[PDB]
Amino acid sequence: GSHMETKGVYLPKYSAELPPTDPSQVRVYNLQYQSDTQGNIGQVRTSTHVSNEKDFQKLCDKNLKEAIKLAAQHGAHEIKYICLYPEGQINELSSVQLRGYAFRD
Ligand SMILES: [Cl-]
Image 1: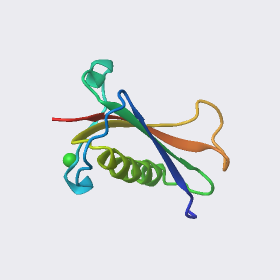
Image 2: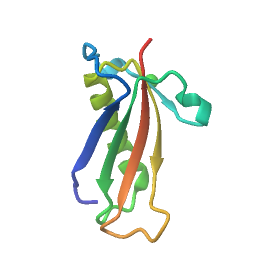
Image 3: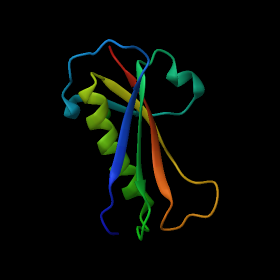
Image 4: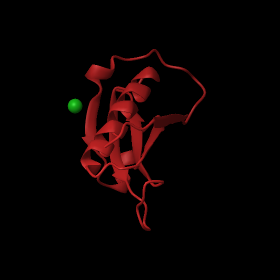
């Protein structure tokens, strides 16, 4: 599929800034349950337009790599994430999204 821009935002629970962490050492887990969010310091949300991509695992991975980088920039030691898709018809103007919760040890 063609390259498309992956946008990301970090949504902190609190105003204090934490020292950045090394993104390669962020621990990454699947977000499986509501209770998994307990204790998080904030959320990371990323998204990429679908365009002509047919491999949606690649779009989820693209979202995840940006989410890891962004969460690490804001001090995360761990993220728990899920990739999300439109409930309606997917087309080239659709977006694949990721919701991640960031944690500090
Ligand atoms: Cl990991």
